[PDB]
Amino acid sequence: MAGKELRVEIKIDCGNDDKETTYDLYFSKAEEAKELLKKVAEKAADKIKKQGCKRVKIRFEKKGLDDDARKKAKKWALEVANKIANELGAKQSTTTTDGDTFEVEVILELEHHHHHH
Image (tube, rainbow, N blue to C red; front, side):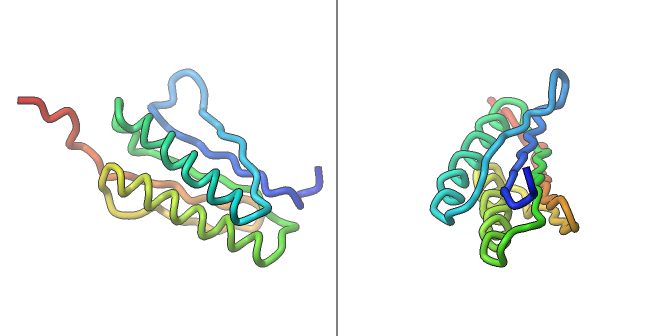
């Protein structure tokens, strides 16, 4: 409880009806960041499979981190966004840097779904 700890809150919008889906993950090693990278980017794409969940929002809290710790989570937010994009289509994520929070939301341009002859 200080703001040293890298608290990542991943918001996956599958059409928010019941509750906002918040995923709790922490970074310290770049290897951990990479492990969480494949977890979030796969599990997000799994939600998109049914509804075409084309709204994704990555929120991350940071303040008392090292320049390296900042770079781990920064590069992370890009690569998971490009992975979620790679699975379905679209272009890129919308990136917003802030003092306390870090908002990178992946707006997928995906109308074309369920093509069945």
